[PDB]
Image (spheres, rainbow, N blue to C red):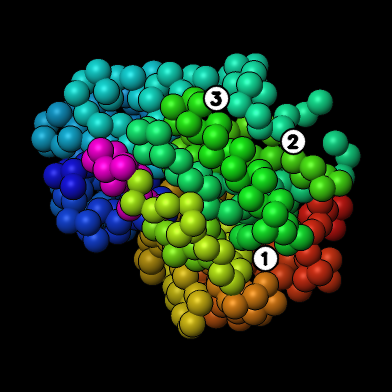
Amino acid sequence: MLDKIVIANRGEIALRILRACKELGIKTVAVHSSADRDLKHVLLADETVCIGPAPSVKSYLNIPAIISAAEITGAVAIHPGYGFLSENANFAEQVERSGFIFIGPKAETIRLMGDKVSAIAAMKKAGVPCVPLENPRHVEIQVLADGQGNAIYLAERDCSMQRRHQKVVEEAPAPGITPELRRYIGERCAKACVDIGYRGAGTFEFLFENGEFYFIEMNTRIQVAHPVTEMITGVDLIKEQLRIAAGQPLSIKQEEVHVRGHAVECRINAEDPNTFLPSPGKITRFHAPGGFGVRWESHIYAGYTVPPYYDSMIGKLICYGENRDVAIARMKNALQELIIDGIKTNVDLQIRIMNDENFQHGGTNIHYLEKKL
């Protein structure tokens, strides 16, 4: 394995990456802003480096600071997580120019898929259906490619519950998607990976309407909702990224990828339910939910202050069951068990969505939540 990596991110995803590193025996370097010294993953990391003041512009987006931290600590690779610099092709290029492994695709591939014009042309050439949409669902295909010619798909996710184009609930697999539709669109995505020389984890986002898929964009990084795919396949997507990055060919064949059960993820945000405006502050009492099929992904703890400088998402609750109904029933109970006092959160909204008759039936479109609210 990689001897030592910099986790070039923060919050829940940084903690997610740290855990995978610990499991693989990879040493961790937590780079953090002045406002993030008390992040759980920072406290758990082997080494820590303060890379700048609070604003992201001068810390988590500060390319020379992050490279310098990686050099001084003797790291060999950098994991960008999601957001921040994960899809910054200039960053990928510099990481590799500086002699590090970038845990993600080649810079050229980031540029190719980061421009909508070049992206669509690449997809059309590959055989991925593009827009040639009033009532669509958001359905996305998870892929893994080793950058060595091997590429697999790991079913799909439905992320149609959104507010202002930001996902609120994600689930896997997508309700209504048959093994044959899954195979059709998955094979096309896997081929596209080979054709573009894709390396690492990635997501093909589609609009899905009247039984047809239409490509919107590729996220050339890990996804916020990766855990739902993990629950239904058993594949640890972060460990796979780390293995691929170490130069290991894919250790999973397509025929070894099986969908079993169902998982739902509720994003937990520090926000005023009356306005949906961020509500940072100090958490005074905290209790995580437990139980069979319950997975809580979050850096928060009792006494932790959510700073004002970053995104409002503070955690993700993921519930798995043998079927969709069990997953939803467990989510209902887990959301009720969750205690986050001292700040405002969207837990009550998540409870309402779980209790929604149309969501319980499934297959609601991308416009549903905003119509409901």
Of marks 1 and 3, the one in the foreground:
3
Question: Is 42 placed left or right of 182 in the picture?
Answer: left
Between residues 28 and 336, which one lies in front from this camera angle?
Answer: 28
- Please provide percent x and percent y for residue 138: 72, 46
Residue 287 vs 123, above or below: the answer is below
Dividing the picture into quarters, in which one does residue 356 lie? bottom right
Question: Is 191 placed left or right of 276 in the picture?
Answer: left
The answer to whether residue 185 shows anywhere in this view is yes
- Please provide percent x and percent y for residue 170: 63, 57
Q: Which residue is mark 3?
A: 113
Labels 3 and 2: the sequence-earlier one:
3
| Residue drawn 49% across the image and 82% down it | 292
How many numbered discs? 3
- Please provide percent x and percent y for residue 279: 57, 53
Of marks 2 and 1, the one in the foreground:
2
Residue 228 vs 77, above or below: the answer is below
| Residue drawn 66% across the image and 52% down it | 182
Q: Which residues are magenta?
A: 237-249
Q: Amino acid at mark 2?
A: Tyr
Q: Which residue is mark 1?
A: 350
| Label number found at residue 214 | 2
